[PDB]
Length: 115
Length: 115
Length: 115
Image 1: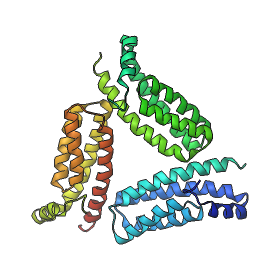
Image 2: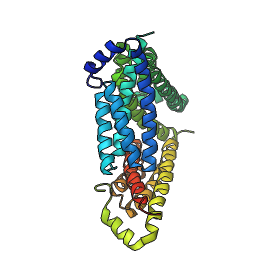
Image 3: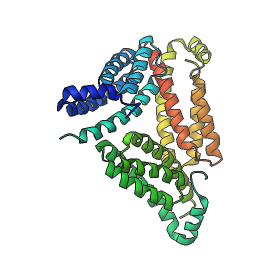
Image 4: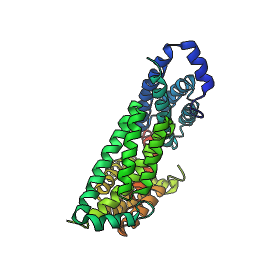
């Protein structure tokens, strides 16, 4: 569902990947759960460069899977961590967890349609 | 306290239930905690059916105990779940956690008035 | 920094404290975390007087370290708890967790500037 998922991106991806598509949804969830775990760890440690790195990785994985609002927040975190501006990091991690839970349920529902 | 609790639902329940009333405050809290744990488990499984049927009971339990804002969220989650419109489920669950925490402390305050 | 930290309260404190300044950043984090844990335990017990007493301490400790928005939420909790008005307690505790998370990462950033 828009505006959380850009059907543009995912319609093309499903068409190419065929039975790999359900594996990409499952993998996206696992890889994003590990990214969020890494961001919380980086936030507690006050590790700006780890926040920036992981944010940038997450931005790309989000964009690959048409999770465009999630990739937006990842970009914000990457750019502010790059400035050393960390005030917003807790609230952006929160925004990422609330947006990621939408994408996760949408992916778990779409996954159910496949064997 | 309005708008969280409808004092006239509760005043009627007090008058009817007499000595049972404090026991109902206590079991509303434990029952609702369990219903929230089951909604989280249902959301992490992507089980729209388990979301729908836990939301509908919590709606009634909330209604029964004059928690009318909490009941209005449960109603929204039940309907969402029945339709399969899961994009709102994470946000509605969090709204039901923040509104239940209000009801919980009001009911713990009220329970202190009884042996 | 602003509006979360009043930099001049802190500029005066580091001028006075010199070498002890980084210890105070560390201490403030640990003191504040234990007081949040105390607030949550008081909220789950429906203990208005524990909420009021811990809220008052935290207001002072926040104020001493230029965390003026955090101290504002603590003041709101102290005043409402004294009046036995506990309907806003859950929300105010959550506002103090989100604001504290900002002060925490800014203090962990600054602490890395010292041995």
